[PDB]
Image: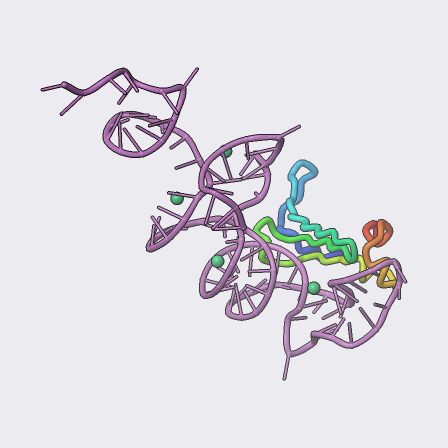
Length: 65
RNA sequence: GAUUAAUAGGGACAGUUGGGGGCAUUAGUAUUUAAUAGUCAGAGGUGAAAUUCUUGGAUUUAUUAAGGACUAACUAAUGCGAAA
Ligand SMILES: [Mg+2]
Ligand SMILES: [Mg+2]
Ligand SMILES: [Mg+2]
Ligand SMILES: [Mg+2]
């Protein structure tokens, strides 16, 4: 099966925490996730990675995706 | 032998008030730029895009540092200064 990497600790009553940084410009949007110490990057998705037209590099749609 | 003492003016004095001024000092974020790490393909900019920047790593996140300016929010028909 899958080889996850989250620390060795599950539990449908044990919450995991990830600090999501979100910068919203009128041109581009960023969505970042990182340790609660913010020194090790995990996930990084920006509107640009989501659409073709530079004007849409902001969009509500690009934010959804 | 020298008028009063001008809701005239000059001085003394008394607590007090002010973003008045001159030297010191002292911060605070932010903008840059640099280090230390962190990823990952796009950043940035416009109505649209375009020159611009970028896996000899950008934008990005955390810590920290250097530097020059600036004093936010409180800051309002409120204050001070002859005015600037
Ligand atoms: Mg003073
Ligand atoms: Mg610029
Ligand atoms: Mg400094
Ligand atoms: Mg005042």
